[PDB]
Image: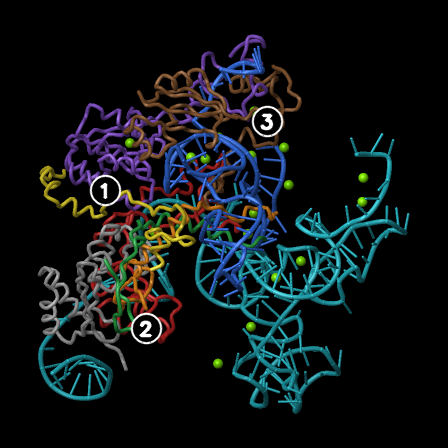
Chain colours: A green, C red, D purple, E yellow, F orange, G brown, H blue, I cyan
Amino acid sequence: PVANVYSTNGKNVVGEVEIPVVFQTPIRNDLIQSVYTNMSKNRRHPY
Amino acid sequence: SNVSNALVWELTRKSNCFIKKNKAGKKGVFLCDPLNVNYKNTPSSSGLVKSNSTNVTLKDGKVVFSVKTSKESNVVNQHFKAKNMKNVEKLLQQHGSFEKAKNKEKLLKKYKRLSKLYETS
Amino acid sequence: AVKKVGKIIKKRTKKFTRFQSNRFMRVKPAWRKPRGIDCRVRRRYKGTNLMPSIGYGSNKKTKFLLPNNKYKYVVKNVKEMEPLIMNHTKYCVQIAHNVSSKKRKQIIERAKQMNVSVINAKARL
Amino acid sequence: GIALKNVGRIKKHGRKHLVSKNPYLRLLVKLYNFLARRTNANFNKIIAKRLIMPKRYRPPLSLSKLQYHMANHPNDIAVVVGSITDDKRLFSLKQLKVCALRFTETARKRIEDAGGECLTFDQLALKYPTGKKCVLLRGPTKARTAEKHFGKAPGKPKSKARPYVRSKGRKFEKARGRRKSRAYKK
Amino acid sequence: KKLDVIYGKIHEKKVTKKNYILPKSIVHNPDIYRIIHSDKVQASLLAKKKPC
Amino acid sequence: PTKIWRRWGRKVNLKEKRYAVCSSIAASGVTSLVLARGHRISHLKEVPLVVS
Amino acid sequence: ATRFKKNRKKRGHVSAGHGRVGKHRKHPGGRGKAGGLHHMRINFDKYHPGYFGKVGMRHLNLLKNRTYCPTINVDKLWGLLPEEKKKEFSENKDIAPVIDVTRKGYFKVLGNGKLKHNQPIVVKARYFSSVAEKKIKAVGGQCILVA
RNA sequence: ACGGACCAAGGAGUCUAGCAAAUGUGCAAGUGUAUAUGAUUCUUUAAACAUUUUAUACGCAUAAUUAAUGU
RNA sequence: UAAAGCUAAAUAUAUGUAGGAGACCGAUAGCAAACAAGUACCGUGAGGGAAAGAUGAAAUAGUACUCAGGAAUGAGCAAUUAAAUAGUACCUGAAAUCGUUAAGAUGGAACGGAUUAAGAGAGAAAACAAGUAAAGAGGGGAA
Ligand SMILES: [Mg+2]
Ligand SMILES: [Mg+2]
Ligand SMILES: [Mg+2]
Ligand SMILES: [Mg+2]
Ligand SMILES: [Mg+2]
Ligand SMILES: [Mg+2]
Ligand SMILES: [Mg+2]
Ligand SMILES: [Mg+2]
Ligand SMILES: [Mg+2]
Ligand SMILES: [Mg+2]
Ligand SMILES: [Mg+2]
Ligand SMILES: [Mg+2]
Ligand SMILES: [Mg+2]
Ligand SMILES: [Mg+2]
Ligand SMILES: [Mg+2]
Ligand SMILES: [Mg+2]
Ligand SMILES: [Mg+2]
């Protein structure tokens, strides 16, 4: 599995690169949402 | 190998930018996505879950014909400009080889309904 | 009593009003369940207010239909009423309260072309 | 009226549904419910039930006990609905075939170096639809420390339960009620 | 391209995340309805039964 | 009365953070998921979309 | 999060779940560990039996760094070696490994378990137990004392 | 038997420390990057990212028992 | 190595002054004080201590003239403004309480639950008619 590299004009295909193995991680919306709820608390200001 | 149609259905059942439910008149729920011939929120009619699909839509003033037919992740979105009944019939033979008859009369009836809509300027 | 028009049956038409709301004006008519010893409504004495229960429920086949014998859908612009082209015999539309007259004219004109009925197509005329 | 117990309504006691929101586990539950229903085999029923249990009833199983349980079942498949852990007390590992929910990295490496293989439950559903030559196993469910506090209260005669104490020593709950020298023992 | 070095496919000092292992899945292939329609499974099913 | 020693923030395990970032990159490569988030990409060719 | 608290379910009820006849009052049995040995005796006796009284000698200035001593059994003793290295010694027969456990954070070797048959091993440590040292000798090894 | 002449607004199981049980998540004989330091971090960012170029900071766990020398 | 002496940094800051900011409060809230607020006022004294924000875009538009009346004030064919039922006690303008007109009831309380009847007010989204034909006025699609 590969991907194409497009030039900045948007039309030509000027190469290809092999898809990195990070893109095969299991997609987990429950875990992402739960981690996001805890992390977004760290930038609050006190009152 | 980390994804399939069933897993895509699992991730998009509830959270989705095309779902619409009516708070008043409690019956009903719709998917308005581009490749949904009906508007049912089911895995067997949603364009995001299916691997091959056809549809007819307005999308701007006129009527537009759409095909998906992507079988090796080659997600191709072909858009054609429907003009009249004969042209739509020709396009169904050209690109809709994967449809049953039952779906084809439904799409033709939908097109016959869509052709009666117009506005000013 | 029971009201029946076609196949639709309503088991009751009167509302359930709050106990003692006819005698004190600080008590609003919206139903609240009575708690408290010696109530005579919590204990089901004869001759007083009735309590609501699950028995008065409606038939599942005819639960949200209007006298029109269709379901109601509320729309806010022209594009929101796209899904109704496939099921134009089971649904009727109503226009939202805060849309202008200019938008309402367009919505009504499209609803006519789709062969869908409008419940309130006489407002702001 | 009529004289029934529990107004005639039948009672059940266990867990009824998944609590977990992991989508892959939900796919597995759907698959094995279908298999249990359409091929009632008493093998798919037990599996479909076990992968709903809470965490404390899916204990880990080590490599040494895995090998010991399969000592008289060569060229068979072991099935576990928990995790497999490594054991540094083993010197050598045989060639085994194992299906389970999770493997730790060290255990997974050790298994494959001896010529065996690791399977997931969607592969065992595909190659062994009715569990032929498959052996079901589970780990210790009453080895958790919390269980050492349960049972008869510590203070009844001949109870083995641990107490809840700040720390441990000669100064922490060892004087009156724990030896004959201070008015009675236990 | 840096994305294969960051996650340890190719190793490089001060770029690769140290001793990090890319996570694994509990399902090998999430297509359950392809498994159901296979011949091996279909030959073990039982005839469809009736409701009441 | 509200106080300043309310616990304002949280601590998050490192491995779960990394796992979530990894699972969020993988979702960025599925055409259907990107569309369902609200992006209008009906005219894109490939969803990973690498540029020179 | 206040969204999920139990008190919101009692919000229209009179007594907030605490009872008509027995109220929720403030300290109706004492403060802290007050009544133990008088009217809390049963709880103290069945859940914390040896609580009252004292036993043993005093130690006036402890200095815990004098007696600090972590241990290890002979089971985990071949497992400190990499598996490919463990393979080489079990193959060849005129060489044996010499392991220094103090470099790994252990001080005393302890004697639970089973060493492999006819596989000599030489172990360095600060303290040994009798059974551990016997098991090391039996398979043809040797213990060494270091400081 | 006590409170209630009437109406509007307000009005009561919360926060922090410490322990346990239950359940969800990650890794697993280990686990938790403390205080700090680093970075082509610096509107947001008081967030996020990193860990010192056969590898001994500390906690809990991996072993018990005895007043105790100890074992 | 006591009974003499000196010494920067890493630490603290419910005070005073200056700067920046927030998943904070929004005029019975937030500091007691959003205003001539530690002010008016009370106590011999030590001390106690409030209530009170909003016309309009513009008043460099704040109400000219006539009639009645001692005046206050009212009315107009007269007058500013988009607007005076925005007229300075000026955005909006609820409830308790009171006035005017109409329609009913009424032998030592009044309201109410169930069920119907007689009046009065509103109502067509199921509570009848697709289509055909002849015009007239529009609005789209394609070759
Ligand atoms: Mg009703
Ligand atoms: Mg009573
Ligand atoms: Mg009965
Ligand atoms: Mg109750
Ligand atoms: Mg009470
Ligand atoms: Mg009592
Ligand atoms: Mg009293
Ligand atoms: Mg009184
Ligand atoms: Mg209120
Ligand atoms: Mg737990
Ligand atoms: Mg000196
Ligand atoms: Mg000095
Ligand atoms: Mg401020
Ligand atoms: Mg104030
Ligand atoms: Mg205007
Ligand atoms: Mg205004
Ligand atoms: Mg009289």
Q: Are marks 2 and 1 in contact (CB under 8 Å)?
A: no
Q: Which mark is residue G64?
A: 3
Q: Determine whether the beta carbon of the residue marked 3 sits less than 8 angstroms from the nearest atom of ligand 10.
A: no
Callout 2, which amino acid? Thr
Q: Residue at x 21, y 65 (%)?
A: B76
In whole angstroms, how far apart are the C-alphas of marks 2 and 1? 47 Å
Question: Chain ID for label 1?
Answer: D
| Other-residue count near label 2 (Cα within 10 Å), few / some / many at <14 / 14–19 / ≥20 | few
Residue I56, by quadrant, is bottom right
Question: Is residue G126 in sight in this rendering?
Answer: yes
SS assignment at label 3: helix
Specify the quarter for ligand 5: top right
Q: How many circles with numbers are drawn on the protein? A: 3
Of labels 2 and 3, the one closer to you: 3
> Is disc 2 in the same subunit as disc 3?
no
Where does residue G107 sit, x and y in percent of width and height?
49, 26
Q: Determine whether the beta carbon of the residue marked 2 sits less than 8 angstroms from the nearest atom of ligand 13.
A: no
Residue I61, by quadrant, is bottom right
Of labels 2 and 1, the one closer to you: 2
Please, is residue C87 above or below residue G69 in the view? Answer: below
Q: Determine whether the beta carbon of the residue marked 1 sits less than 8 angstroms from the nearest atom of ligand 10.
A: no
Question: Chain ID for label 3?
Answer: G
Residue D140, by quadrant, is top left
> Is disc 2 in the same subunit as disc 1?
no
Residue bearing the label numbered 2: A8
Locate the N terminus of chain E by quadrant.
bottom left
Callout 1, which amino acid? Lys
Camera-side residue: B69 or B105?
A: B69
Q: Residue at x 18, y 47 (%)?
A: E33
Callout 3, which amino acid? Lys
Where does residue I34 sit, x and y in percent of width and height?
68, 65
